[PDB]
Amino acid sequence: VHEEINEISSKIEDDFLSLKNQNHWYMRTVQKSIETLEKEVLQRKKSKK
Amino acid sequence: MTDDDLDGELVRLQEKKVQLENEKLQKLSDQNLMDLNNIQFNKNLQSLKL
């Protein structure tokens, strides 16, 4: 069971070493999409103004 | 940050637009007075005709 726990540590090491930050840039990309959307909203408000 | 100045300008625009209302009232007052004076002049003219 202890060896299985070590194997679990190896699995965790596998999942961790699998990839660096990726989806974080997708979250920042969503924030950028919110920025462009805010640009469209500000442009619309500028149009109405 | 660019939105802020636009907001401020919008507020100043709101005040500037808020002046034209009182201006319009002061204006229209002369129109009403002109109407009343017109009525009085009409009656007076009729009396002169009599």
Image (cartoon, coloured by chain):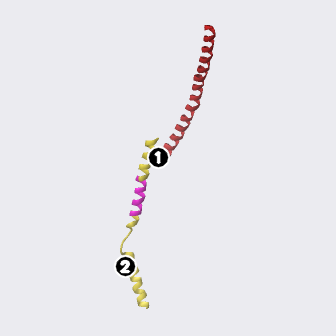
Chain colours: A yellow, B red
Front-most of residues A13 and A34: A34
Q: Is residue B37 left or right of residue A11?
A: right
Image height of A2 relative to A36, above or below: below
Q: Is residue A29 magenta?
A: yes
What residue lies at 61% left-to-right and 18% top-to-bottom? B39
Residue A16 found in image quarter: bottom left
Element under label 1? helix
Residue A46 found in image quarter: top left
Rendered location of residue B17, percent (x, y)? 54, 35
Rendered location of residue A6, percent (x, y)? 41, 86
Q: Residue furthest front?
A: B50
**Residue pointed to by mark 2:** A14
Mark 2 → mark 1, Cα distance in angstroms: 46 Å
Q: Of the residues shown, which amino acid type is indicated by label 2? A: Asp
Camera-near label (2 vs 1) is 1
What residue lies at 57% left-to-right and 23% top-to-bottom? B31
- Start and end of the magenta stretch? A26-36
Image height of A6 relative to B48, above or below: below
Q: Is residue B34 left or right of residue A46?
A: right
Tag shown at residue A41: none
Q: Is residue B38 magenta?
A: no
Front-most of residues A5 and A26: A26
Rendered location of residue B22, percent (x, y)? 59, 31
Image quadrant holding the C terminus of chain B, namely: top right
Q: Chain of mark 1?
A: B
How many C-alpha atoms fall within 10 Å of the one at disc 2: few (<14), some, or many (≥20)?
few
**Residue pointed to by mark 1:** B2
Q: Is residue A26 left or right of residue B6?
A: left
Element under label 2? helix
Q: Residue furthest bottom?
A: A1
